[PDB]
Each structure stands twice: as structure tokens, then as C-alpha cells.
Length: 212
Image (cartoon, rainbow, N blue to C red; front, side):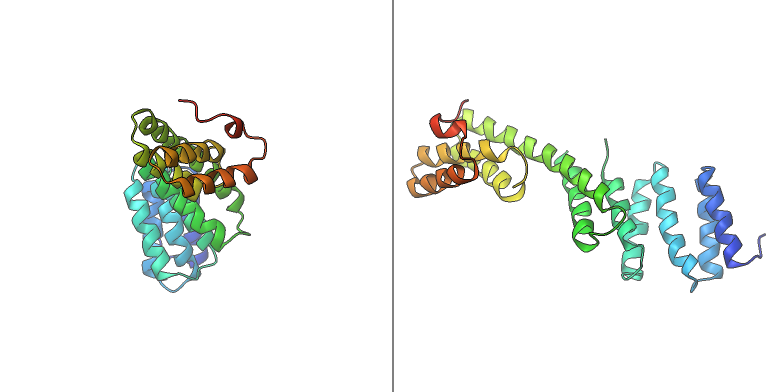
């Protein structure tokens, strides 16, 4: 029983959140939006609900709360924190979970570049693209050693095309160049070296070829 105002009911649920009573904090957040469905605290309450699930092991419930929040209140002032919260949930310490996280932070940085979470989103994007780039690069070397030059090139094009800012770009060009030579696409090979020549003037791969 708690027939109070909207201001206190929110401040009460917000207190159970700090003390980590996520089970009771969520129960109070539901009373709030049932008893004051049109209040701004109800819209904010839906965010706090997802945050509570994330702090528990129920990450699937958090992703549902976020998507419902995004379709109901697409123009909410705290939409930026919603996207950032989705990234943390998808983020965990493989390409699937890692790429879905990158796409989450990516949508946030280009929709709300001035968000108080943008810098942290960017910082996490960098760590993820480095992990993905290093993975695709590892497969590129694998298929190179096995004479699978087409399969290898596909990995190199991905790095060149999708992870243009990572450090793996240089070696991906040298791989792509050598790859185009083996399968006799000489125009694409020359074009690739033309890119390596301009973007990396003093690259070891200009004087040497790829080093398996």
C-alpha cells in the first residue's frame, strides 16, 4: 500500500535502485506507470526499469524494455541514454555480440553526438572495431596460407571497407594486392598498390611483398 504523489513514488523507487533492491524497485516502477501513465516520471520510469534488469542477470528483459521504450517514446529527451544502455547490454566481457554492440553505439554517436554518453560510446566503438578488425585480419592470413586467395581477399576488403580507421588497413592492402596478383586481376592489383602508395607513403609493403 502506497497511495502517494508522483514525486515521492519516483523518489522512492529511485532509492531502492541505489540499495540494489532491483526486484522491489521494478515493482514500484510498474505501480508508477499504472497509477500515473501520462506523467513524465512514467516515461523516465521505463528507462530505469531496463537499467534494473541490466544490473541483474536478466539481459533479455532489458532489451525488450528498451525496444518498447524506443517505439513508444521515440522523441524522448533521454533517448541517447537508451541507445547507450542497449550497447552495454549487448556488450559483454564473438563477432555477433560484438558487432551488434558496435551498431548500437554507432547509432548513438551519429544521432546524438553531443550526448553526455557519446565519448564513452566512441571509446567502446574503438575497442570493438579493433577486436573485429583483428579477427577478420586473422582469417585473412589463414586463407592466404592455404592458397584460398578469393576467400582471403574478401576478409581484406571488409577491413578496408568497414574498419577504415583501424591499424589493420595497411596490411590488408598488401594482402589484397598480392591476392589480386595470384588470381590474375592485374588492374585491381595496380589500383590497390595505388591506394597503399598514397595512404602509407613509407610502407614496408611497397619494397617487400606480403610476409606469411
